[PDB]
Amino acid sequence: MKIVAIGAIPFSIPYTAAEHVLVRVHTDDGIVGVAEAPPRPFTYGETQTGIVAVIEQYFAPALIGLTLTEREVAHTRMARTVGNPTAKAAIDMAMWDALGQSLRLSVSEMLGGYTDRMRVSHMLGFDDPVKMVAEAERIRETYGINTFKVKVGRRPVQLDTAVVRALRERFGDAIELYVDGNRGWSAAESLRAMREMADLDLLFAEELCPADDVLSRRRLVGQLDMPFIADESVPTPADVTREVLGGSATAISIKTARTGFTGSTRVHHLAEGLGLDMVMGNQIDGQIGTACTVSFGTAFERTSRHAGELSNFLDMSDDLLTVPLQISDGQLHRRPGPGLGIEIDPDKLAHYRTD
Amino acid sequence: MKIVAIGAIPFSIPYTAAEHVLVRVHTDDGIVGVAEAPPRPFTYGETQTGIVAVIEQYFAPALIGLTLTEREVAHTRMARTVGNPTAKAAIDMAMWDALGQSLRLSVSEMLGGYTDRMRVSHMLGFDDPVKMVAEAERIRETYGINTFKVKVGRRPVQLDTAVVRALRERFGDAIELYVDGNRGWSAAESLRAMREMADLDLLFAEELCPADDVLSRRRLVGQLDMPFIADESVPTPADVTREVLGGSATAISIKTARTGFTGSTRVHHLAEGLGLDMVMGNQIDGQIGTACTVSFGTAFERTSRHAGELSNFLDMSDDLLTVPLQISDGQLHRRPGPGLGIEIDPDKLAHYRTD
Ligand SMILES: [Mg+2]
Ligand SMILES: [Mg+2]
């Protein structure tokens, strides 16, 4: 189980576009672990070109020679390089995939195996209330999804509060609802919006305003009833500690795209120890990334007690798996096979790769 | 004064190697502003390949068309992309260079023009005390430098405290001394080292331990007499606020390599308003970057009241300027010419570029 090579292949798939990087960890046993790295310059500052570069130029040469059971050595070596979250996460998850295949165990069970499935949430917004209601009905009827996260951040705030209210009026208590502003509103606008929706039983408020508007962010978080999920502002455990102790976050988003499995376990244990809720998020992941999210989320009780953002891949026109993921009865099961339980379709990769 | 093009040229110059990126902002007036971006994967996570990529693929197309007097528009647009500090800083400084050339004004005077020169500090360490003393004598006698920053972080700590003590015994109060651990020591080791050197009158303690060892870092900072300079942990104003209010920093390093001139002004004003000392740092800069550091540092009283890390370029085997920078009587003057007061030697660029 020694790493003999690590590759990074850029690929592009149009949306109904995902310009991700397929990361592959090759072992001396002929096993190949895989994962994807989604470049999000507006969240982490990584680019597709940059991810391939850091992996080929820095991470690959630093990890070749290590066994699949020296994860902490790999973790420590990669940690020397600052940032480049998805690049590091992809390598970690590909290593875990390879390990699982080598031991004939799923990543989920190796991580803890608490359960075998997660409830799925769907995100929507930035359109008319009538259209949003129509989409929610379609998604719920088609996939059984009962949890919806409304993307907000428009001005006037009434444009978004109208969407959330329309959804609650249509489904009543039959669905779960919460919001994510992606730092789009000011703290003051965020408070006015939440106050207007005080009767809609929103379970969480996610990154309504910039965490970097430090003092106003802290004031807002202290004014809200529900937990305030920090996402882009807590990419590392140290950020979790600073934002939580500082009062700018009262809940934590865990995204395997940025913290993989080794790092995500560090985030889960920190959040559990501190006593904070956690939710599995989506980095606008393809099916490879989604398979990773469910692999981790199902391993623990604290992550599986909440729905996970696992439906974004449906918006892609195609994907790289030989067997596509399926959402039924509003849930997604962790794959039955060893490792991530997935396989890359050779023809799909050949058709979508851009190198 | 409209930007018509922005280029990023990778180059490499061996040390007596600097793999930086020359950034050039072209205007419709035929003026070309310049600056460099030093890729520091172990500090910011940027790579030489990554810097060129983010500039060519994201920043250049987003800035072409803006005038040199729409700095806040450029600042806001670049801010959409997370991280990539030196890439952004280089573009900002090149824009300022172009503006200065267009108005026949030096960057220093446009920024405030408080003074015309800065005292220079030199960093050394990681060798035997006798050799370190010899180097300090040489540097002081050769350039007149009277401020030395000892790089520390080795174990046992006695190896570094011995170096600092040897320097103080040799020069007495004739020189200024302080230390920078580059996050190399644990907080506990850092305290023991500083206590051992309590009689050596160190003016500052810089990043002795990781800022990410959050609680122990805060405890250490509160135990030390002198100001504790945060550097790699405060790359943005928001980090300055979080680290300062959290107690993990009691002084601020300003490096034009990561915050340029527009961003550095934001850091200076924040630090001045909060009431914290600030020091101009070095990102292992070449002469282009050093010219930028002095341009900014001389503009304000709070930055010029302390020596600036401005001697690292001396370790390079060559550089790209037509007229090299000169340190005399332990000081460096801001260039007399418009903009940064520098010009790229065509033959040097042709010989060292790697594209
Ligand atoms: Mg989010
Ligand atoms: Mg430093």
Image (cartoon, coloured by chain):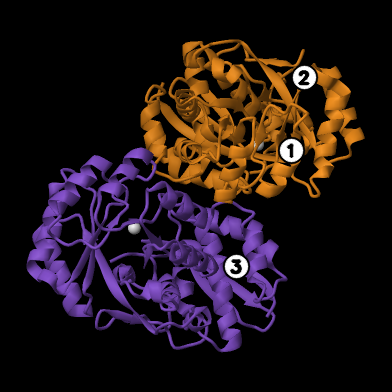
Chain colours: A orange, B purple
Q: Are marks 1 and 2 on the same chain?
A: yes
Q: Residues within 10 Å of mark 1 (few under 14, many from 20)?
A: some
User: Does residue B164 appear left or right of residue A116 in this picture?
Assistant: left
Q: Position of residue A208 (x, y in %)?
A: 67, 42
Q: Is residue B104 above or below residue B155?
A: below
**Residue on which the image places disc 2:** A146
Q: Chain of mark 3?
A: B
**Residue on which the image places disc 1:** A195
Q: What element does badge 1 sit on?
A: helix
Residue drawn at x 73%, y 38% as measured from the top left: A194
Q: Residue furthest right?
A: A130
Q: What element does badge 3 sit on?
A: strand
Type of the residue with mark 2? Asn
Whereabouts is ligand 1, in terms of quadrant?
top right
Residue drawn at x 83%, y 23% as measured from the top left: A139
**Residue on which the image places disc 3:** B7
Type of the residue with mark 1? Arg
Say which of marks 3 and 1 sits in front.
Answer: 1
Q: Are marks 3 and 2 on the same chain?
A: no
User: Does residue A184 appear left or right of residue B124 in this picture?
Assistant: right
Residue sitting nearer the eye, A251 or A83: A251
Number of numbered discs on residues: 3
Q: CA distance from mark 1 to mark 2?
A: 24 Å
Say which of marks 3 and 2 sits in front.
Answer: 2
Residue A285: quarter of image: top right
Residue sitting nearer the eye, A188 or A137: A188
Q: Position of residue B100 (x, y in %)?
A: 56, 83
Type of the residue with mark 3? Gly
Q: Position of residue B250 (x, y in %)?
A: 35, 56
Q: Residues within 10 Å of mark 3 (few under 14, many from 20)?
A: some
What is the quadrant of the N terminus of chain B in the image?
bottom right
